[PDB]
Image (cartoon, rainbow over all chains, first blue to last red; front, side):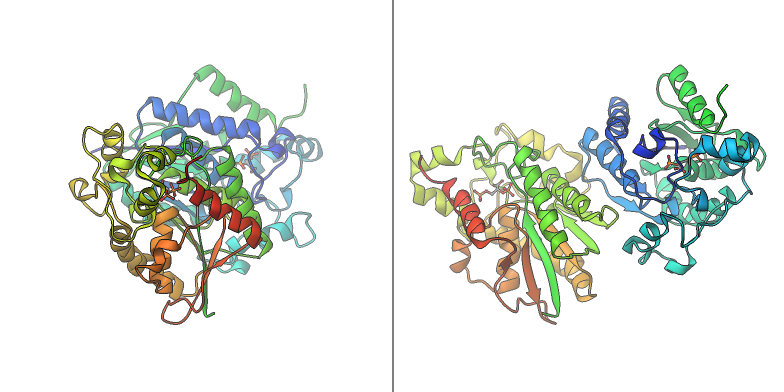
Length: 255
Length: 254
Ligand SMILES: O=C(O)[C@@H](COP(=O)(O)O)OP(=O)(O)O
Ligand SMILES: O=C(O)[C@@H](COP(=O)(O)O)OP(=O)(O)O
């Protein structure tokens, strides 16, 4: 048989309007991001989706996005599970910094490696970093399945997959094989990591994949939980392609 | 108090202005009801509550109340679990009717009996009722731990406790004993039901218990999960007392 699930990246936040890496900083959605979530819900309602389970990260923007979608669907009673393993990639010391500023300071090539490469690891975030405390003093990281001191201080996309894959195999994949309709409300790079795995994208090719925000991602899997075909985006394709470019352009020097 | 837990009933719903028995009909919170939820979260945050698990009914107003509370607490990550067993008492045929109009026509004492009695079972809702289809056709009841045809069509407060107690004993109680701080976002009568049980309130005394909306109810339990003392409403008692009278007045003429 074949199985379909929905994956999506939450919408806008104050920091991305400023083009700053947010990552593990628990920023809330802004008005726009909230609306993008509701629009995703309306599209899903149009397709008459009836979810059985929802998985999110422990970053509140991921959870609020799910809640907004469920409300649009009148499905607020559907079980939700949140895990740090779906958290956006940890950008380490790059957290809070302006992407275009990084391109000017280190060049576009380096920035593209930091943002999209598979193996490159961002410099780790140190205790002196402006957002260090706000992150590691939060109780949500004191009750994860890994000790607080063992949580990453930065992650390469490969690092993300290593901590996300076990969660997918052990808690999400089984539900898919049981025919459950699943919604994964994740982030830009945690989503790319999952896609890289399910579609068997190469270490090299994954660098060219950029996901637009607030856009339902359609993915169909076979009996072996491997992608039957490339992931697709639900909505106006031209607008989605333009949004993908805007994300890419955030790491480019003006011209 | 070896264990402490918070329970509360959600604020005003979409039918509150009309003062109609909502019960199993899935109406959403109105503007005021949302604020009541937010104020609850603020009050809980001021008292340093850190929840580890939240239980709600499957009625959206109860879930939304929990979500708003969690947001004020910055605890949106805390696990939430929902069950029809925490649903408000099923008002049967009385669903959709105006409380005050009933009081006018049948007498305040009669309506008070229907609302707070422990043993009186309201007339069952019938297929001809305006809100029957809307309730029993909903997918949330298709995936219950009980067959659709087995779900009640009306419930006395005693019936409510009977289908709520199992959920408490099997899912909630164990967590409390594990030291977890729990929040129960329930309803006017399902909350009364749980209180009767936990505080060992008599069949007669339970009739005089009316719970205010949007007010956190602190319950302190011992090793046997039995209330050590009476439930405590967290907030200004005078304002809380008025919130209670508001509920009682819903069944009074004028
Ligand atoms: O790291 C972040 O803040 C972005 C991704 O940024 P880029 O890797 O695309 O630059 O993830 P999001 O929080 O928007 O889901
Ligand atoms: O819908 C209901 O019947 C009320 C209780 O009504 P009364 O027994 O207080 O009249 O429960 P709620 O929806 O507010 O949680």
